[PDB]
Length: 49
Length: 143
Length: 146
Length: 97
Image (cartoon, rainbow over all chains, first blue to last red; front, top):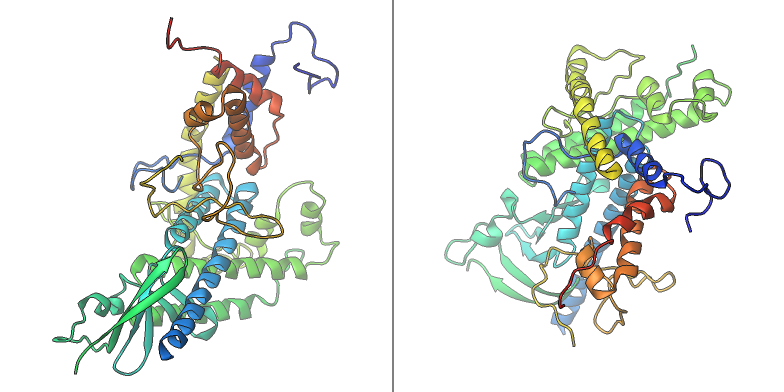
């Protein structure tokens, strides 16, 4: 069901910790995402989300 | 006969404002997506523009329904439209096509009355159904 | 010699300055609120910057080293090239909103004292932000791993 | 009939935008399927789950996250998002014994 491991191109090995790989892959490009207005001035966000 | 002929003219112009607003929204949406996908600037320099564009897109969405409240004119025969947002023609020295009702010169729309006309001749009001104006009513000012 | 400047910059800047002068006239007439005027000026200057960038891209020869580095995908982007040889464009005040006066001098020409002063707002904001910015990504990564 | 009565005037009506018709905003007389959005904006995950079911809310969450990531030029395979989304739907609440 998991399918091929993207790192090797073949069917995923039994025992591979896919959860940690997925979490790290999702979290690594986080710094490139647009983030909240860190300075607390202005009206509360959510409308200009 | 005059009434629907005037109404058709009003429907035409108001349709013009919607067309101009739609062109503006597409312009902002294109740049909003472009900035998200690539900006080339520093992180704060990048997301700072996105907030402004998102603010502009939200501004347009709030306004595209019942955009024009009604026509108005001055005793000098110059005609003004009052609406949710101010729209100006870049190609004609920024002739005001639509004036935000909060604008200083738009105040006579609410303040003007027959017993004390603020240099405005005939106020008008618009009924709307989604975008199109259904019908209007007039109100004379002054003698 | 390789950092070329598009010759159409002067006319574009003059035309958009005339447009901004028209904006000022209409604001004096009382047709715009302060925020509306500022947003309209930002709107004009954004397309001014885009037009200057278009002229820069259309002017450079294909074999110029500066454009060669970018077009090949090795590094950089056309925005940095525009900043270097075009115009710095609009900048953000400390509160996080665009100042209505653009920086019309490129880093090749040399920014004046006050344009350089106002660029420091954004520079400092970014430098101070990055450290806290990494924290949110760390937070999300910790939770996703958990 | 199912009725909603107090939707604010600020919210833009959802746009269908038929490729050839370019109808845009849905209007009176249109036909909508189960769970189709009405106003442009985000959809509540809980309401989506309640209306459609677990097999559909997972798809909605995965699509939303992937759209958010790929809009900014980041490529992540859907399986990584699905691995996380699976853990959210792991429990069942007992409404009656």
